[PDB]
Amino acid sequence: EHETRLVAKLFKDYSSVVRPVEDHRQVVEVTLGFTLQDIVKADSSTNEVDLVYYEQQRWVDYNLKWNPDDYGGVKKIHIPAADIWTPDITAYSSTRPVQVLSPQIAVVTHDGSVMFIPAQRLSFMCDPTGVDSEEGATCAVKFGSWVYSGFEIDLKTDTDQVDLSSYYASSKYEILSATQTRQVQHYCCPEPYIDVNLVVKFRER
Amino acid sequence: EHETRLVAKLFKDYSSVVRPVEDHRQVVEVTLGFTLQDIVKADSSTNEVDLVYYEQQRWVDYNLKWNPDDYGGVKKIHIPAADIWTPDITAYSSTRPVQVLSPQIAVVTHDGSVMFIPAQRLSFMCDPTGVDSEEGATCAVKFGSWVYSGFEIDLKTDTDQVDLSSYYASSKYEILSATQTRQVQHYSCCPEPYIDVNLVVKFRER
Amino acid sequence: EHETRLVAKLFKDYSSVVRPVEDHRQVVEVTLGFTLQDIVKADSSTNEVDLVYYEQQRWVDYNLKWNPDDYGGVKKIHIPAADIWTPDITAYSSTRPVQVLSPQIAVVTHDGSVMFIPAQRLSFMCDPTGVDSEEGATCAVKFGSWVYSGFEIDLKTDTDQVDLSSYYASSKYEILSATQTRQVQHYSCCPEPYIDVNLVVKFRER
Amino acid sequence: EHETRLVAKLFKDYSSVVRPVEDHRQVVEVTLGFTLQDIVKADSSTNEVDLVYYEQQRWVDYNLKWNPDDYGGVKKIHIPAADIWTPDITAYSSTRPVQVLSPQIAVVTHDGSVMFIPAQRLSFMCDPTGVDSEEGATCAVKFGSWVYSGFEIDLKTDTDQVDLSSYYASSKYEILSATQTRQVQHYSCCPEPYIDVNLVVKFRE
Amino acid sequence: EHETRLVAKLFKDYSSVVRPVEDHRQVVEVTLGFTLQDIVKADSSTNEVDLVYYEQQRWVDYNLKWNPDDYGGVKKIHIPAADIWTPDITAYSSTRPVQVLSPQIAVVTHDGSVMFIPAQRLSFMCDPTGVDSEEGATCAVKFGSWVYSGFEIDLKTDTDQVDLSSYYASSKYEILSATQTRQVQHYSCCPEPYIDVNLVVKFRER
Ligand SMILES: CC(=O)C1=CCC[C@@H]2CC[C@H]1N2
Ligand SMILES: CC(=O)C1=CCC[C@@H]2CC[C@H]1N2
Ligand SMILES: CC(=O)C1=CCC[C@@H]2CC[C@H]1N2
């Protein structure tokens, strides 16, 4: 009953369209990490490549905090990502809607730290020329906020190495390397824009 | 809690089915601009071509204005497009439903300026005959309000040049030219004129 | 402000599930018209043909009337089709769910007249045999109410000549002719007539 | 006016999650009937076959009754199927989610009689070998409640002969025969018997 | 009347986002078992296989208990899966969103025991090399909670032997053997163990 009471209280006046910072001049810092599971398909007739991965996202939500003492020792809740503010992290060169492969549930801890790890299949622009060689081919796709600038959302990675420890061992494609690198840029605008570049080098097995 | 109170205030009595003008005799002026990203696929057996692009849309919403000073200095809000009035900009010769490639969130400034930029994959009617020649092939598609006449929605482009600076350099198709041009049309259904922006693309295998 | 007040008042006690008539013994008269844009493909291996068109529907909704004078001169509103009653006009021999290619928004005038013009892509049962000859091929599909009798919904066309003036000029298929013909059907099952509009298309490879 | 009041009354305390019977110990009798319109496709590389048909369903809802005199003489209402209790009739050997071709609207008569006739496209497990011969091929698929046992939902047909009077006369396949036959089955999960209607079609090019 | 009354009481303050245990320190034990129906397709150019099956899930919901004597003798209710708490059982190596082939309705008994048996079509990562030989091919996929650890959701099977008694006998592929085996995994992201059931399928061309 404690958890049920916690959730109702937390979400009574909660807004999912407002960046969850105490002061609006503050940035929301989002840590991003990829676990690449499979290169399913590299289509040289359309230059689309298909990846399956999951994408760990972490940030702090100021308004989703509580003292576990007040609620039977409850330290975590599990909430549909749709009901909380989430960062709108988007692939910048997809060619199809990302397909979701996992339940869209975020795990929130009593200190407000959110963990959200959607599994995804992405088709993105990539010319696989060289994939049939020992050296392999390389491709890249950028991920970032669609509507928030670097003053509103800041992106970080914990490491520039993509997690390959769960890559499908019998994929049609061997992974040779995969990095995830933060990049800052300016344009019209006084404000920095941030993305994480996902670079993959791979070859037919 | 400033932004939260702002949003609750703005949307307490807001209706998304009502054109956002102080006076209904007034027209909503919408600026459209296309950013072409990739010609993914051209199908000569059905004469459908698939485009990936961003569509920049800008208009003013009369009822989404506020003074930053009364709300902690908040200057912009980010609202799902489904929750505000939007221009029903529609491709007139699509052959499949448009696929949405970005979050559907509109950015709204304190002066009521809305900016909404959906990325899309569109299949539309297009004969790619000649795409394998120096001259290439030429296709076009009209974008405009499906249900609002020119007395209700009017369109403007900032330039007739389509933005090609984000076009996929390794695309199977090279863009020779791409324009976006405002047009007026009449349809047998309705006595009033309707406005569209005609996207004309000339392209060729690389 | 006025339109918002109008809309609030009209849909306070509105039911999208009841036919919009003063008394239930009255019939709703729906006028249908097709504007055919493209035969995208004709599949010889399954005998399915894919059409892109938009379908003008008009009828009067008794409970959607107002005096513009009481509402700042507002002459019409734009309401999502899902929120008003609509005629459940359905193809009787489709092979896939219809794909929606336009916003689902109805236009309602102050005298209650509703205009709703969905753009659609439809696969239906059709044998393309002879499409590669000069005589061409002929196919047909009936449109009508799924759950309402002829005493509840009646169908009319303004003309039996389909609007072909917007047909895609570089389609893989030329349209030889297209008619939209009201048919009245009597089944032993029912005393009441059943009414459909028969879309007949003669076509061939360009 | 009258109808709007009838509908508000009927559904004030109605629940679409509760079998519509006065006595819980009573069974809901559902009459089931198929109208086969077309065999669209027969895929010999995956042994899937695609049917288009109308599925006629009929039952009584005890709580959707009224006297026409008390409501301006309205004798029928037309309600989204999702808003009333419906039998969860399911194909047991489909290989894709069934596609709905018609409006999901049920017609309820004042005596509580419900008529619901979804048109569907179904891909189901079927080996079309011999479809190119005079003998043709024969496939079958069961239809029944997914979660209600024979003690809760019973199925019946009015005839064992599938209705072929609407069959597409220029289909790639002609129907040699098509029957619909009530069956009782037991499944490993549950001790109660379950009811289905077996659709058997023999066809050829 | 009784059942309606019971359902209203059960769900007045029910939360589907809260694990249905009395004490939050308690684990929810979920029994899983697969019934394989068909290997539809095995794609050697992408190494994906398409499997049709249904998946029996059983657990106890602490808050969905009642005395049948208090409610006309009602012993079972039938509730859409989406309206109760359910374990988020997920295939860990799927390559397409899973397709649901059955109504999503859970059966709940008066002692709170829930039975939920979704039928599904799954594409998952699978190298069919050898499927055209007598030894056939072997693939595996793990099923488990996505967001709940072994301290919150545990899994059990009744048997390691997968139910093959309903397998389609005219499938393009035959199943030589199939096992379902409980396992415990550890991830770097999270300090707690996670439970899965590993489905292993050996199969070949018929
Ligand atoms: C009001 C309405 O639906 C329309 C008005 C004219 C413009 C195009 C063609 C038909 C449709 N969209
Ligand atoms: C309760 C339930 O979902 C079921 C009960 C038995 C009938 C068929 C097979 C498994 C499933 N549907
Ligand atoms: C919390 C969450 O979403 C997850 C937790 C660990 C178990 C697996 C791997 C990552 C993801 N699912």
Image: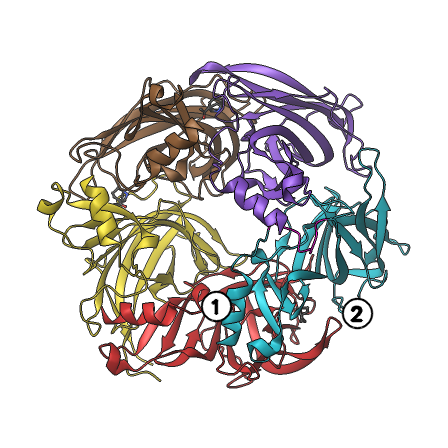
Chain colours: A yellow, B red, C cyan, D purple, E brown
- Toward the viewer: E181 or C178? C178
Left or right: C69 as drawn, with respect to A158: right
Q: Is residue E182 left or right of residue A100?
A: left
Point 62% across, 72% down: residue: C76
Amino acid beneath label 2:
Ser
- Quick one: C38 or E134, which is closer to the camera? C38
Q: CA distance from mark 1 to mark 2?
A: 34 Å
Q: Nearer the viewer, residue E84 or A41?
A: E84
Report x, y in % for residue B107. 38, 73
Please report contact status of discs 1 and 2: CB closer than 8 Å, yes or no. no
- Magenta range: C17-24
In the rendered image, which residue does mark 2 sit on? C165
Q: Give the letter of the chain under mark 1.
A: B
Marks 1 and 2 on same chain: no
**Residue C168 lies in the magenta-colored region:** no
**Ligand 1 shows up in which quadrant of the image?**
bottom right
- The amino acid marked with disc number 1 is Ser
Q: Write the residue at 55% across / 72% down.
A: B174
Q: Determine the image quadrant of residue C29.
A: bottom right
Dot 1 beta carbon under 8 Å from ligand 1: no
Residue B189: image x %, image y %?
73, 70
> Image quarter for residue D188?
top left
Image quarter of residue B175: bottom right
Most extreme residue toward the left is: A69
Q: E10 or B91, which lies in front?
A: E10
**Residue tagged 1:** B16
Above-or-below relation of B93 to D133: below
The label number, if any, that marks residue D136 in the structure image: none
Q: Is residue C23 magenta?
A: yes
